[PDB]
Image 1: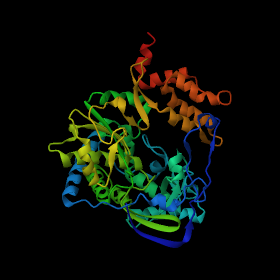
Image 2: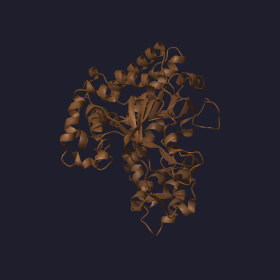
Image 3: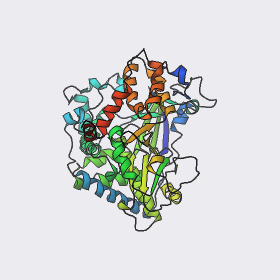
Image 4: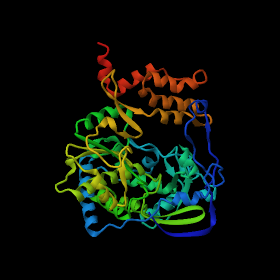
Length: 476
């Protein structure tokens, strides 16, 4: 986005912290080229000249203003995608009750009871639980007051910059490439969920190529569904973006919000309004207040869904800006945020699409760097989606999500104190797909210290998850 103003204020919003990640027994064995991101400017690992503040906001290099002709085309694309989306999902998009927004509904998890509350609550020493009764699904006086301002469209707010405590490749760690979470006030998240939580739950429940979204999918069971679909096309491309979320221009955001969340599609008039509050935002970092025009805040409610919707419209837009007669059936795709897989029987020239994506402020390049240009002929077995490859399981003939061993090793090398056992059971679910031998090697360091699921048990669990009938047939 475009930083239009920077100012210093009296109130200091703390951002520096201590990492909660520590090495595990596997770290000494795998020696991963990864480490916890720097959470302080004083971190000795940072390179000379690295100012955490600056690096974090360096992604904002402008808000691309689209021509009248391009915005008209973009609206047509947004409306065409919206037509497909609501045709598949239906129009039961009315507001969620306060209780439902807090507790959740089928397809939408409940809100986090103890995560950051945002501003100005964090400066007042108030935690989320002091504002909302998460057990009974009710809100206190402070939130109630804020909701009234939102119903009247008079609500104002500032985002709290939060450093993401996570593992990253060391090269990025040293460069100070610590990612962030733009924490919005809890009442804002609550109201956003009230306005579009219904729609979000439905998108989760209907994930797939038809609506171009993988948000809410379960790789274990869905890779077979996604794999068989894409294996049917002549060409498959996996695209990479640079700062996808930060480079969404205000024109694209506003237009998308205007065409997708219309009252005629079952949404309350305030759904478009609350989403639009995300376009021009104020961010607090220590004593600084930075105003940014354009770009999607990080971690805001429905972030994955919004980014995925934009990704779908971007592809339709770019193809139509280059070719004539392009429609939704000209190609097929699936995306999760900035992650994306596109396919078509037509020999689409993605290299030529670069300038068209640039008109949106987005920079695309092939996911496969062993080629300074897009090529034809790739298949579903050559792409990576959600950090997973599409491999055929020889035992069943079903596709399974396989993660790179270097990635798994890195994941296994660090953990928050007291969570290792639970983390291992989770990663085991990801590692089973790498096969018996690699599975054994990856968990070898933990043997005897923690309970490691047998490869056999996880494989059987997976077969039934992907196809219950197949699991049953094996018993005739």
